Amino acid sequence: KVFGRCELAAAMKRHGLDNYRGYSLGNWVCAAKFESNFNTQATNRNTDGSTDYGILQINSRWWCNDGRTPGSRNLCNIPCSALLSSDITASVNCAKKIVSDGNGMNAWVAWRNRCKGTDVQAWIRGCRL
Ligand SMILES: [Cl-]
Ligand SMILES: [Cl-]
Ligand SMILES: [Cl-]
Ligand SMILES: [Cl-]
Ligand code: NA
Ligand SMILES: [Ru+3]
Ligand SMILES: [Ru+3]
């Protein structure tokens, strides 16, 4: 599923991401924009052989099981394919664990490079939230 911007903002809010760990909703929408272009089916291979999955590009090295990332963990206790669903529940629940890990949203390199320190409220501007 390719979400609309405001559609994704509303889903993320309903699932408790608004201000989770202090990160306003615009931060999460901005991260999703640059990680996946709002496409739940996005997958991308990393140089280390792991793969990133879903609207927040969650990495099989630590967070989900894809059966093909040697020596990895599955700290969200989910198959990576569950992160590709039209229903964002699994991605949100796993993102909550990731952002609590110590480095906040810096875990998402694209958030640090493209969202951090910008006017992230623009990503929810106009949305009926
Ligand atoms: Cl915001
Ligand atoms: Cl594996
Ligand atoms: Cl699995
Ligand atoms: Cl933080
Ligand atoms: Na894994
Ligand atoms: Ru839902
Ligand atoms: Ru850690």
Image (cartoon, grey):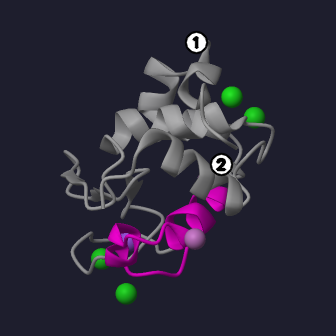
Amino acid type, mark 1 = Thr
Mark 1 against mark 2, which lies toward the viewer? 1
Classify residue 81 as left or right of residue 9: left
Q: Is residue 79 magenta?
A: yes
x and y, in percent, of residue 33 in the image: 40, 36
Residue drawn 78% across the image and 42% down it = 19
Amino acid type, mark 2 = Val
Task: Return the mark for residue 118.
Answer: 1
Q: Does the numbered disc 2 mark a residue whose Cβ is under 8 Å from ligand 4? A: yes
Asked which quadrant contains residue 84, the reply is bottom left
Classify residue 113 as left or right of residue 38: right
Q: Is residue 79 above or below residue 118?
A: below
Tell me the quadrant of ligand 1: top right
Q: CA distance from mark 1 to mark 2?
A: 19 Å
Callout 2: SS: helix
**Magenta region, mostly helix, strand or loop?**
helix
Q: Quadrant of the C terminus?
A: top right
x and y, in percent, of residue 102 in the image: 71, 44
Callout 1: SS: loop
x and y, in percent, of residue 99 in the image: 65, 48
Q: Where is mark 2, residue-wise?
A: 99
x and y, in percent, of residue 88 in the image: 49, 66
Q: Is residue 59 above or below residue 119?
A: below
Q: Is residue 81 above or below residue 120?
A: below
